[PDB]
Amino acid sequence: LFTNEDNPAKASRARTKAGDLRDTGIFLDLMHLKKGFDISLFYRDIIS
Amino acid sequence: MERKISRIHLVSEPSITHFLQVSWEKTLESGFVITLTDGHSAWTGTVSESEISQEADDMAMEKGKYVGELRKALLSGAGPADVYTFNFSKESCYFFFEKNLKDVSFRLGSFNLEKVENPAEVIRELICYCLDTIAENQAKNEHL
Amino acid sequence: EELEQGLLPWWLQLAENSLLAKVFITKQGYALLVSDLQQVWHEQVDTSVVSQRAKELNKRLTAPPAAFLCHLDNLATFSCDCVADALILRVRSELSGLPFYWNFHCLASPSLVSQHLIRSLALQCQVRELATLLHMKDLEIQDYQESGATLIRDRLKTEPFEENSFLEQFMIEKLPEACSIGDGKPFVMNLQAVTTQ
Amino acid sequence: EELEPWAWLQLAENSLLAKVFITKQGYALLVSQVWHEQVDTSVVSQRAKELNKRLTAPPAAFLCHLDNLLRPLLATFSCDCVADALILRVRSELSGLPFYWNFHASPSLVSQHLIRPLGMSLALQCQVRELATLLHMKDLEIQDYQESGATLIRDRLKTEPFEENSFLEQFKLPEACSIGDGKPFNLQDL
Image (cartoon, rainbow over all chains, first blue to last red; front, side, top):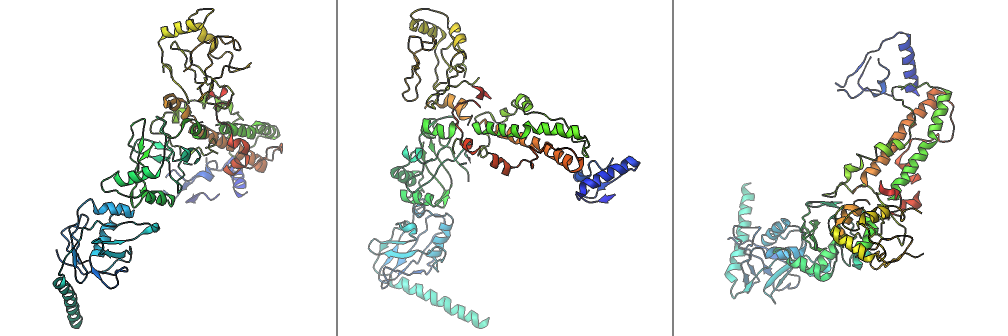
């Protein structure tokens, strides 16, 4: 997945569904496109 | 050392005018020689240092603006920024032009002036230089 | 001293110390109240002292007393001229078009001004406020735990605690952060100045 | 001026904060603004012996008996309170206090001990804010429990996260002008 900054209700359901998919055997990968280690707040737990 | 034409408008003496035809040395922030005339008696004198700023503190205004305002009043053109009532006192030989803020007598500069007899030739040269500048400006306008 | 005791918020940074500026300049005078943390003084103002300071403090400085009085009533380094018992304080402010060359022939009377500024419970009042906001909140946490334990951000999760932990190991090594009286730890904060109110 | 917890007595809201440091140089009592005294140990010994007309004892026993035993926790006291001067020196029995010591703008100990606690007050407000922001871990936890946790809520302190607006709403306004004189919070030594 690709995004410059984290966008997020919507966030709760998104995190729940992401956790469910991770449980189903799905891997995730992402880096913020600003660069440093600054913007991963809304996706701290979403990614592995 | 030159004489600059500054006809300060005397509210107290509308009949007897006063020109602060300053003959300044090569200094502005320190004491500068300011010369005055009325039509029948000129007031010359040498202004000392560290004493002209005592009245500036009496004025209780900014420094640096003091030097520029002294130049404006002494040289041609009274400055709109800090208008002083041109009370060039013949009764004391002390041409005090002051901005009496907050309705109180605040003096501007210690000018030790002395009354003389014959400023006729000096005033002649003053207005002659004025109109010579006028004539050369007119010729400049013509060729321009 | 009536012009200071009956006259009575911040933190003027002087040459060697930062002191609260508890001065209320009026048309009848002005007395700067500075808690130097070293000496008790008496800030007094009179027309004669204003006149003499303005006229002879500097060779190029000469002003009437009404000038300073009124133009402070209408009102950036600070220099300290102190003798440790009769401080002739210099408040170099932007006054009269120059750095304000002034002599405060000083702090103020010990008892009344000590009550006003020197001599609290309100911090402990917020302590009980936080305790009350915490006290049965832990009970609600146990209610939640009994109902369930799911938490999306389970990474950020810890058991309910009490303020006693901070009363034990945080009422130490923390107050010593601002504990010495030299220049002065920033006193611009601590408005709730409860003793002043 | 030799040694210099907090001990305080309630009377007239004066600067008399009845804490005394056990020392051989007389009294370091802060029941005073704060006065200071420096006297030789021997002079203290014979001074107490002269003022005691019934028994002569070393000052250590007096210090250990009168440190924090009777005044703080629980008949007119010898209060010669002129210019806030607590002269409790009467050679008789006043609530069982056998302390006989002639009690004589002194901001040394005031500045190092009284002006600083209003210097040393910023960190206590900092710790108050730290407690407030620590309670905001509870806020997100209860929000997630009540939104996605589908948990059972006590419905007593289901409150919005603590704010400076809530800080001023709670802060207690009659005690927002609280009595700062030396009163607890004896226990005010912290």
